[PDB]
Amino acid sequence: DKKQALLEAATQAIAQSGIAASTAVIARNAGVAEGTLFRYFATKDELINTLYLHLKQDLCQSMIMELDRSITDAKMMTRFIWNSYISWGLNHPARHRAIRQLAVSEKLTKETEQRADDMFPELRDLCHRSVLMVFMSDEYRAFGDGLFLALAETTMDFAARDPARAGEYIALGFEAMWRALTRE
Amino acid sequence: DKKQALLEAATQAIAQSGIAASTAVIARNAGVAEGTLFRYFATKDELINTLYLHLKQDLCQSMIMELDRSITDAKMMTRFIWNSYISWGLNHPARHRAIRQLAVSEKLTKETEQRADDMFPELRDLCHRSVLMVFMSDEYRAFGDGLFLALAETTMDFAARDPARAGEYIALGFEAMWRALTRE
Ligand SMILES: COc1cc2ncnc(Nc3ccc(F)c(Cl)c3)c2cc1O
Ligand SMILES: COc1cc2ncnc(Nc3ccc(F)c(Cl)c3)c2cc1O
């Protein structure tokens, strides 16, 4: 709860001012001393890693919940997941803002990254099925996510501004992202 | 010289804070009275449109000075422009951040979109031949540039973070942008 509050405050602080966000700020917003933040989190790096798992869990519950398992077609499954992630982001703007910054960032542990993929096994298989091999590689895995997230976050800004054409933005965003990242 | 000072200070504020950037902060960092900004630019929208054409004009000159007209394959020609844009963004981080927020904004006038299009008549004509028709359309043109600027800024962020792989990021980002935006 005091942990939960620090994770809420960390989502708000990071989305607004990115991962350079002050542990001191988070604590005051948390309604505690900085010393409490460090009791709960040994490092700012530990809190970033813990927060990313927190937000990715929150996002995958969304995605898991919406996944019609009758579907097998790779393109069809990914579109579904695209639609889940976008709608998750319209509904939680700060969560989307912090998670996109966290996902690309250098300070994620390998243990953090493994566990995230555990959270939705269906995506890891789909990416192994569909994505250009270069973006599955250790060297450019982060680059391909950063490209997915850029196109998703663009698709989101246009969607919010223009509820009227939101469906076209999502359709056009997804097909753009699919050509970008998958085998031709 | 008050105007050129302000244009530069508007660049730094809108890069940091998006178009939400306060005219109060712009004038102070510009070294002038907020009242004085308003004399040069009667409204915020006014400042936004002028700043946009200013950055667009600086970037297009760079792409024109660097363009090798001995390049005959339309794909290689665009890679060259992408290279110069990325090169420009890495040399000028605040200009690219700012030009992206401005380019994808409701606040730009049709007359601004006209003057901006004509800064490079042949880069314009190139897109007319090469880009997916939906992304040339009245409704979705802003979204196409939106998808392009997101792919380019992510490319610039990875090149800047990890200059060892700078070349492959640029190269990968171009091919992803190419499959994203263009006719097949
Ligand atoms: C087509 O390839 C991808 C599809 C994806 N779908 C959904 N999520 C992806 N990645 C992703 C990775 C990390 C994240 F935090 C978020 Cl919010 C999204 C995807 C990454 C891909 O490379
Ligand atoms: C092939 O598709 C495009 C290629 C582009 N190349 C270079 N520049 C484009 N637009 C652009 C590039 C830089 C900018 F700052 C702005 Cl505001 C717009 C392009 C837009 C496209 O849709």
Image (spheres, coloured by chain):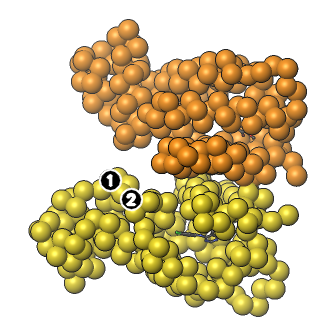
Chain colours: A orange, B yellow
Q: Is residue A126 left or right of residue A101?
A: right
Name the residue type under label 2.
Answer: Ala
Q: Which quadrant of the picture is home to ligand 2?
A: bottom right
Local SS, label 1: helix
Q: Which residue is mark 1?
A: B20
C-beta proximity under 8 Å, tags 1 and 2: no
- Which amino acid is tagged 1? Ala
Location of residue A16 by image quarter: top left
Instruction: Estimate the spatial distance between the alpha carbons at disc 1 and disc 2, rounded to whole Å.
Output: 10 Å
The quadrant of the rendering that contains the N terminus of chain A is top left
User: Which chain letter goes with mark 2?
Assistant: B
- Residue A34, given in percent of the width and then of the height, sits at 27, 22
Query: Of residues B169 and A170, which is closer to you in this image?
Result: A170
**Neighbour tally class for label 1: few under 14, some 14-19, many 20 plus, Cα within 10 Å:** few
In-image side of B54 versus B177 (left or right): left
Res B16 seen here = no
Dot 1 or dot 2: first in sequence order is: 2
Residue B82 lies, in percent from the top left, at 65, 70
The residue pinned by badge 2 equals B15
Residue at (58%, 32%) from the top-left corner?
A: A87
Q: Is residue B180 visible?
A: yes
Q: Residue furthest top?
A: A1
> Where is residue A8 drawn, in percent x and y?
39, 22
Left or right for B30, reference B14: left
Residue in the picture at 64% in, 43% down:
A167
Residue closer to the observer: A58 or A33: A58
Q: Is mark 2 within 8 Å of ligand 2?
A: no
Tag 1 subunit? B
On screen, residue A182 above or below B110: above
